[PDB]
Image (tube, rainbow, N blue to C red):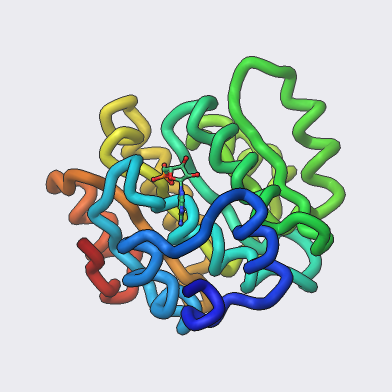
Length: 202
Ligand SMILES: Nc1ncnc2c1ncn2[C@@H]1O[C@H](COP(=O)(O)O)[C@@H](O)[C@H]1O
């Protein structure tokens, strides 16, 4: 169960309340490794429980810390919103802020949210780069970087954006996770250059 995987009591209560009675296979396989700080390469698709697989240990990692601690990249506004909603449910009542940054709104609204130093930022690669270029997303405290559906981000033209983000965020103290159903050459290059010999989970 989630307790036996190493998850704290308050987070487990929140998971139970959202209907997570038992971990999924990918959560059982990933979570103990994610908690150990190891880089993870997940070959998984929606339906597996992959949001919980990265999100649950991320909550355990950032709770009680200050400033932007983690960045999750998603291919679409819709997936970003869904991931952010789940993370807010996981972390219910523990003082964790989650901020979403994607296109379609003026960037001023997001800048204001980022000034408060949310522990978790979830965004699309293009919008994230806008904040990096404006210095409104500080990378100095970012200790976890998650690429959700890396193949889909590449299908939408974001490979250079992903490369840039992975190069710009300091790597030595960073834990990186990459989830993707397919791994074409461009994605394999990201793993080889920007990750630390990740554990492969299938
Ligand atoms: N351990 C679990 N028990 C029941 N439902 C879950 C569990 N983990 C994830 N889910 C749900 O599984 C669906 C697929 O999640 P994902 O693969 O993260 O897109 C989502 O609706 C989640 O809420």
